[PDB]
Image (cartoon, rainbow over all chains, first blue to last red; front, side, top):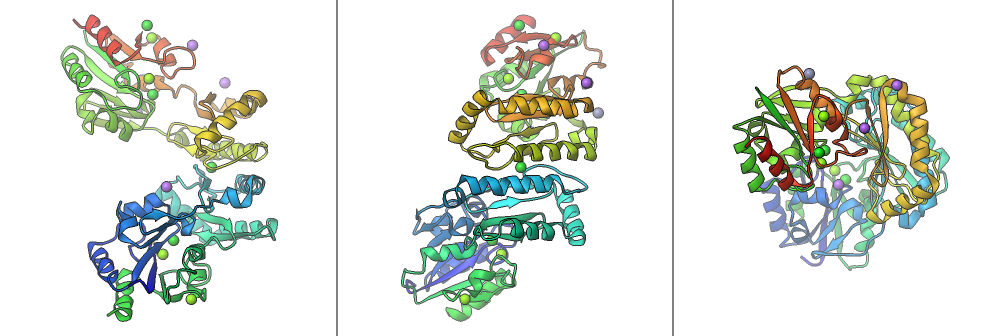
Length: 243
Length: 242
Ligand SMILES: [Cl-]
Ligand SMILES: [Cl-]
Ligand SMILES: [Cl-]
Ligand SMILES: [Cl-]
Ligand SMILES: [Mg+2]
Ligand SMILES: [Mg+2]
Ligand SMILES: [Mg+2]
Ligand SMILES: [Mg+2]
Ligand code: NA
Ligand code: NA
Ligand code: NA
Ligand SMILES: [Zn+2]
């Protein structure tokens, strides 16, 4: 076990998106854990991982990397911590926030709500409609956006305004744009693993194509990456690697 | 003739943000045999359930979460209203756009997230962001007292929007509350004023100017009594309904 690590994205890879892991998947993972170390990484925060993977998540995985590894647990205890304001500084943080606030104020939408800017440890989540919107409101924006390309234009303008300042901008989900320091995608968690001496770090994700949130870690030479369709696919591949 | 005892929750029926004691809940059910009872609070239905019990709608003749924007009578849901329906989506968005642009032009030591929190009865607007840490709240609060950041913001909001039927009030250490005129606790009185009660007694702990019971207390449709704690509420009710 100790020589290799199977590192899994959570949403769409270990669980159905935003849903609790199944008892079958949980049983499979602990059996797999007898043959390899296992870890989980995702953009969601620790409390969301607890809700989906169990309150005892840090005991069920050898590594737990909420927020792409900006928060990190090894063997049930916290590793070092970093956050966006500590890396970027308050001036750049405020420039980013001010630009996004002013930009959103000039977008004409059917509806606006609240939580246009969600401040997290490893990123800002920015939404023209507001992340507190209801499901009916979220789908309405999503369908409008696929026609008007509001988020695509926003991302392009952000890249122009902040070129060279060390930030990455990405379309996220149905209503948001993710703003984060370059390299603070899932690859960040590799910082906690690359010197541990594992013979192989396998990675499994469901969004490995360009623009997806597994793409960079999937293509990173430090991992042996696999694309999965759903948790059943993850099991099938893992059974082949660790019979 | 028929009377109604209408209670604020936090600090009146319970300790602030805490579950009702078994003592008070038992007293209320006895009192209910002599007068109708109801509860009103700014918190949402699920918070009332957390503090007053998941069966709250069956233990009170009236339940008014969110100041009565949601209303229950005799265990049944009556009707609902929200800020976007009352103002219309265009005005909501004009208000939100103005606040976002304004906040972007305030120079602060730190900005965080949740500058606009959207609720069905109000917006909570914060130049620093409602997600900020406790240390950051104090830093902003103290800076604001010297620089008058929220006072200037509220003045500009009143100038731009008050004709849309909105009230703006400084709230807590970091926020500005934005809500339609009369959407304080008085809102729930529309569900009661034509019922034919001889007296609507009201009980609350924040009945002075600035407190969230002040307007409903001073409204002529209620006979208000100020309480210092749940035990004081029980004392007064026992005198009114021996
Ligand atoms: Cl993710
Ligand atoms: Cl209240
Ligand atoms: Cl916001
Ligand atoms: Cl009094
Ligand atoms: Mg995924
Ligand atoms: Mg690779
Ligand atoms: Mg009170
Ligand atoms: Mg009165
Ligand atoms: Na969270
Ligand atoms: Na007026
Ligand atoms: Na007054
Ligand atoms: Zn109604």
